[PDB]
Image (tube, rainbow, N blue to C red; front, side):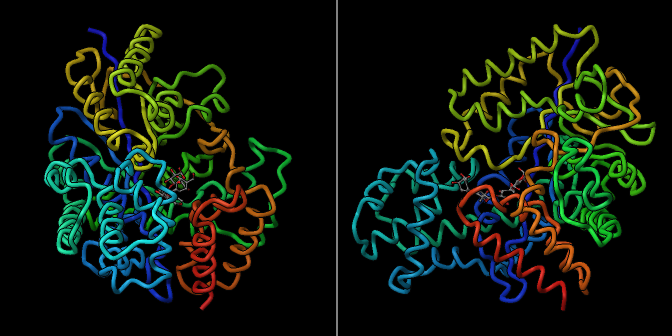
Length: 477
Ligand SMILES: C[C@H]1O[C@H](O[C@H]2[C@H](O)[C@@H](O)[C@@H](O[C@H]3[C@H](O)[C@@H](O)[C@@H](O)O[C@@H]3CO)O[C@@H]2CO)[C@H](O)[C@@H](O)[C@@H]1N[C@H]1C=C(CO)[C@@H](O)[C@H](O)[C@H]1O
């Protein structure tokens, strides 16, 4: 029978929140996503007979390991552990501000949270509830089953009960890297990596790549070559991947799907056999092309193009859907894809694996469990690992000679460079790399720092600015 090959590729990344001087983690997002998604996303493979593929950045692996060993000095987390009698007025404001930010998300829908947020002042026991419910709001699928009776209480938590939650959370973190090894060794999925600190590789090699799609943009003067650092990002990433999995990575996910002719050349030289990028890149690069086909880039590397609609549905749209209606729509589009082509199509669904579920009901567990079990019983859909997709003779293959440089955000680099606020950061980077002495200059090259520049007065913009400027200063010493 004709089949549709489905490839799931989840992207797990966190910037280095660790201040180089104090060694203090200024944001808790590595810890919260570790307990909520970084372990439970591949743990689905133990309960559903499908294939899921994952990408892990080396910077996230670095932070996961530090949290697992207990060495991470997370300032926000220490306030949670601290008995509310020891909490200072400043610390309590952070806890209330954190709750206010995530108050809207369905994973924060606790009746107790409504009372505490509306209360004018909080005593010790109310703070204990606020400390623990913030912890329990980020419970993953695995620990939601184990900590069920605690989560049904919903209030009146003791300090020891809180510490039990932290203890169970740190057991998950220590096991998080093990399951990624486990799924890769057992053949249930393929695990890939990215250049170390999630940098924009095409910009590092040739900053002129921005003019490929946005010709009239004004970028700062790049008086320095970042081309050698772009190899350092790739080379050190493969070395870190070797530490975890005992082998060099053959598959890589370019950060922000950003690709270029020169970027693909550098990936090929470093032993990368396959990567993926956005289908808006496909439309800019190839005349009349389909994303449902394996692509040979100049007979050097294999490239796959994600389905932007299918991926953006999971990451942005389905959060406001019932689990049944969401999966029914998702399968319905695949059936339309199945009928639309005379060949057997391969569909690449690639997106961030941790940031959409916060806005789903029950962290999207009903959505994922319904979709994963639905895909199991659909015979015409064959979930494939990245390695399986690369050796599959049933997928059509085409040869392309060039790509127009750009990210998955509108096919251009404007979200990271182009306006005064973003251009100013690159001038800071360019001048710092002129006097850079150590490798902390690599951390400052991450796309996240330039992501949050300008845009708006979003939460933690001051914190991200503080981290980037601290890394720039440390690189010059
Ligand atoms: C402020 C924001 O911080 C967190 O974000 C990090 C994500 O967890 C990571 O996935 C990573 O995102 C990058 C992706 O890897 C990449 O594929 C591309 O999408 O770019 C992303 C950013 O460059 O790194 C992020 C930090 O830079 C945290 O998880 C998230 O919850 C936080 N969001 C807050 C701000 C808003 C804006 O409305 C809302 O999401 C929430 O109210 C806040 O929690």
